[PDB]
Length: 191
Ligand SMILES: Nc1ncnc2c1ncn2[C@@H]1O[C@H](COP(=O)(O)OP(=O)(O)OP(=O)(O)OP(=O)(O)OP(=O)(O)OC[C@H]2O[C@@H](n3cnc4c(N)ncnc43)[C@H](O)[C@@H]2O)[C@@H](O)[C@H]1O
Ligand SMILES: [Mg+2]
Image (cartoon, rainbow, N blue to C red; front, top):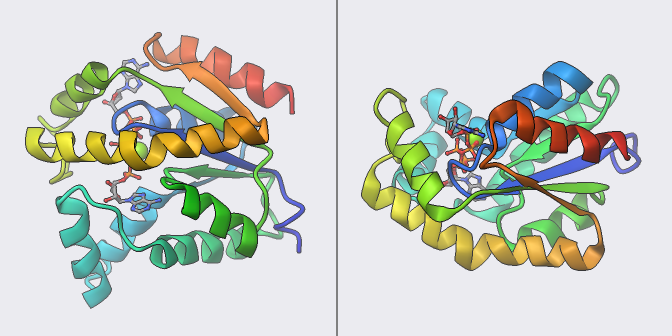
């Protein structure tokens, strides 16, 4: 039960808002264990498994993969690091209110949610630029629009939920990367 007593930080924001970017800075500075739902899912794809093929199809459409699948991947990763971790940074989960609730039922309660806030047009620009070079098949304009629609519909209520909980710190991800990280640092330092 090292885990349920562990420091757990949720990182929530739209596609291309800068979640991963900020999380890499957090890792370098604070040394937290970075668990990205996207990275865990893409790792399953990379394994060549039949599960991986199914997840790949879902992610290519810009849709949410089943709750149990991603939560179980995250839980397993947390357990594998429970003895050595300085704290957990959960990046890209939860993306619906039910994902937050099941995480609290099966794992533990977050002490902080970092709301990486960016405008829709900013996210589109960022993702199209990244899509010029990235290995992501979902960085195309049509799928980008689907990802955004899902974000506002399903994931923004997550932000509202943890605002009601009282643990959200909003960071302005339209500033320069280091400037955003200053706000991130402020929030983490106050823990
Ligand atoms: N919980 C879940 N449940 C069900 N399904 C799930 C799930 N999680 C994932 N899935 C499935 O997996 C798919 C992929 O999800 P996932 O990969 O987890 O989420 P994502 O939001 O699509 O991730 P991105 O990498 O696109 O965005 P990011 O916010 O991390 O931005 P980044 O820092 O890279 O930055 C983006 C660009 O902007 C640049 N940038 C960042 N910040 C700045 C800044 N301040 N100024 C200028 N440029 C910046 C960056 O250099 C970069 O080029 C989902 O669509 C879904 O299908
Ligand atoms: Mg990311």
